[PDB]
């Protein structure tokens, strides 16, 4: 149950959320064959924000290195424990 | 109003997301302007995209291995082959091609689209008026008109990878600063507007229409003021130029109280305590960005530029110095008087304006 | 992949609105398809949604403090056992 709470905590989740909302507005506009510029510009800037957050996620690897050094920590602890 | 709104939305979408520089996006852009386009394989490594219209042919060489544009060539089907599509840089032996630069130096197609829209305008509206010839020669006629009128302005073609006739002044550091850009624009207001060829005659020292039979319809010669940008905006007396010649009036839309900073400076008591400011303007100040200088209005270029230069050197500096926290300072449309100490007018030389500002700064500091 | 397809379809929308309503409707349906698969792919994977900032610093601090206390106790053991 806490998983979804953690997922909602990171910004890019909200980013995909309002990106979906903006495309929903755009499709509603084109359904009414009345394309509103503000919806499209909101869509493009939200997409750009998505893409910058896509870069920001990548520099990931730090957590992975922390994970391997954590495994090193507990394996050293177990070794010294059996010692 | 639906078509005008749709065209305005299409222009907005074209400007807001110009697309990435790819062969497919360049082809789609050319097709969106009604240009005929074909792709040829010159080699296993090189493809050419050739695009054509009535007069213009543009070859774009694409390196398939590098994912990059290698070359761009413009060819005219006019009897005039001398159209300058290179940037005018003083002291570089390599004339840098505007079209190639717009596809290699920029992150997007916006620079290329603007330059292509300009070439397409000349193509569509050239017939017996050849606008490629006339626009090239016009830069020489304006340069001569300034020499004959003793105007200290430099004329360059094609500045910063953009088509246009650029009018430059010497700035305080001897650096050239653009004052205005002259170019052709579609006349949205009157498709029947006759645009004639005007030549500057060395003999008469005037603009002359040699061939009243040589006209194009639905085009205007536009003078755009290049703001270095609210304090860097140029303001004109409302009666300085006929309202029919004003293409773009910056309407301060009715929800932000930006008077000219000049008029707010007649209303706001936050002055240098040494100066009593007196307003002697008879007219309202309006912000004008674009002028129609077509036909008989080519004489106005020198008057508009003198005002723009006087406004930058005198008015804007007087305002900057008065606005930084008793002598009477009278400010009018064409003259400024500091009590009995110093005066300058719009018809004085630039050297008189500089001396007035130096003396004014020494008193206000 | 949905990102480049979204980009491209976005651009032929903004380049050619003068296409007949058939193309506009079909292309908008295509974008709705791509974002539908986008939201699905977001949905099944918890790890990405977690990916989708001081905690990393706190983990680094705890790792370095446990490392230094391990080094100190090992130095003490080395000093004591050599007798």
Image (cartoon, coloured by chain):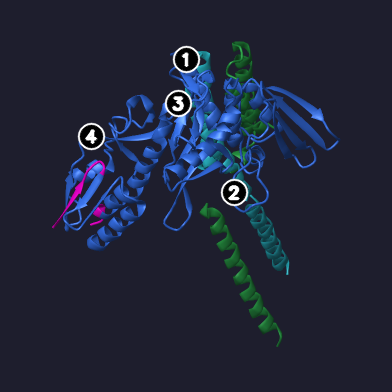
Chain colours: A cyan, B blue, C green
Q: Chain of mark 2?
A: B
Q: Nearer the viewer, mark 3 or mark 4?
A: 3
Q: Chain of mark 4?
A: B
- Quick check: is B324 in the magenta stretch? yes
Residue stretch rendered in magenta on the structure: B322-334
Q: Nearer the viewer, residue B108 or B98?
A: B98
Residue A26 x %, y %: 52, 22
Q: Nearer the viewer, residue B305 or B4?
A: B305
Residue B276 x %, y %: 15, 52
Q: Nearer the viewer, residue B100 or C38?
A: B100
Q: Secondary structure at mark 4?
A: loop
Relative height, residue B317 to residue B114 (above, below): below
Return the residue at label 3: B295
Q: Which sits earlier in the primary sequence, circle 3 or circle 4?
A: 4
Return the residue at label 4: B283
Q: Which sits earlier in the primary sequence, circle 3 or circle 2?
A: 2
Q: What's the residue at 29%, 56% (across, down)?
A: B357
Q: Are marks 3 and 2 on the same chain?
A: yes
Q: Quadrant of residue A65?
A: bottom right
- Residue lying farthest right? B44
How far apart are labels 3 and 4 at the CA level?
A: 27 Å
In the image, taking residue B147 as reference, residue B327 lies left or right, namely: left
Crowding near pointer 4: few (<14 within 10 Å), some, many (20+)? few
Q: Chain of mark 1?
A: B
Q: Chain of mark 3?
A: B
Which disc number belongs to residue B89? 2
How far apart are labels 1 and 4 at the CA level?
A: 33 Å
Circles 3, 4 touching at the beta carbon (< 8 Å): no
Q: Which sits earlier in the primary sequence, circle 2 or circle 4?
A: 2
In the image, taking residue B58 as reference, residue C61 lies left or right, namely: left
Does residue C52 appear anywhere in the picture?
Answer: no
Q: Secondary structure at mark 3?
A: helix
């Amino acid at each position: 149950t806490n998983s979804e709470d953690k997922l909602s905590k990171v910004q890019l989740y909200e980013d995909l959320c309002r990106y979906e909302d903006t495309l929903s507005k755009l499709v509603e506009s084109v359904d009414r064959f009345k394309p509103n510029l503000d919806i499209a510009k909101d869509l493009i800037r939200t997409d750009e924000a998505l893409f910058e957050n896509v870069k920001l996620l990548a520099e990931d690897n730090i957590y992975r290195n922390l994970q391997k050094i954590d495994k090193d920590s507990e394996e050293l602890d177990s070794k010294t424990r059996k010692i | 109003s639906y078509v005008e709104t749709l065209d305005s939305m299409i222009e907005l979408f074209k400007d807001y997301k110009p697309g990435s520089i790819t062969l497919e996006n360049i082809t789609r852009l050319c097709q969106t302007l009604g240009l005929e386009s074909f792709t040829e394989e010159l080699s296993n490594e090189l493809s050419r995209l050739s695009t054509a219209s009535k007069i213009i042919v543009i070859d774009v060489d694409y390196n398939k291995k590098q994912d990059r544009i290698q070359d761009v060539k413009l060819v005219l089907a006019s009897n005039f082959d001398n159209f300058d599509y290179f940037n005018q840089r003083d002291g570089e032996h390599e004339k840098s091609n505007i079209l190639l630069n717009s596809l290699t130096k920029y992150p997007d197609l916006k620079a290329f689209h603007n330059n292509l829209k300009f070439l397409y305008l000349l193509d569509a509206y050239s017939h017996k008026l050849d606008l490629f010839k006339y626009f090239t020669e016009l830069s020489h006629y304006i340069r001569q008109c300034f020499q004959d009128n003793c105007c200290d302005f430099k004329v360059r073609t094609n500045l910063n990878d953009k088509f246009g006739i650029y009018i430059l002044t010497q700035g305080i550091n001897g650096k050239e600063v653009p004052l205005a850009k002259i170019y052709l624009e579609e006349n949205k207001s009157d498709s029947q507007y006759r645009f004639y060829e005007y030549i500057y005659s060395q003999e008469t020292k005037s603009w002359i229409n040699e061939s009243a039979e040589n006209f194009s319809n639905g085009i205007s010669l536009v003078m755009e003021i290049v703001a270095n940008a609210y304090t860097d905006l140029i303001w004109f007396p409302e009666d300085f130029i006929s309202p029919e010649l004003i293409i773009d009036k910056v309407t301060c839309s009715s929800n932000s109280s930006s008077s000219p900073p000049i008029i707010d400076l007649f209303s706001n008591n936050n002055y240098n305590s040494r100066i009593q400011l007196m307003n002697d303007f008879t007219t309202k100040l309006i912000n004008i960005k674009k002028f129609d200088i077509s036909n008989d209005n080519l004489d106005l270029i020198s008057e508009i530029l003198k005002w723009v230069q006087w406004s930058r050197i005198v008015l804007q500096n007087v305002f900057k110095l008065v606005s930084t926290p008793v002598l009477q300072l009278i400010v009018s449309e064409d003259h400024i008087i500091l009590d009995t100490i110093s005066e300058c007018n719009l018809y004085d030389d630039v050297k008189c304006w500089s001396k007035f500002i130096e003396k004014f700064q020494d008193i206000v500091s | 992949e949905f990102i480049p397809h979204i980009f491209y379809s976005l651009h032929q929308i903004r380049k050619d609105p003068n296409n007949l309503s058939n193309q506009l409707e079909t292309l908008t349906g295509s974008i709705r398809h791509r974002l539908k698969l986008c939201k699905s792919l977001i949905s099944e994977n918890e790890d990405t949604k977690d990916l989708l900032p001081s905690e990393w610093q706190d983990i680094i601090h705890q790792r370095e403090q446990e490392l230094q206390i391990k080094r100190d106790v090992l130095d003490d053991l080395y000093r004591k056992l050599q007798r």
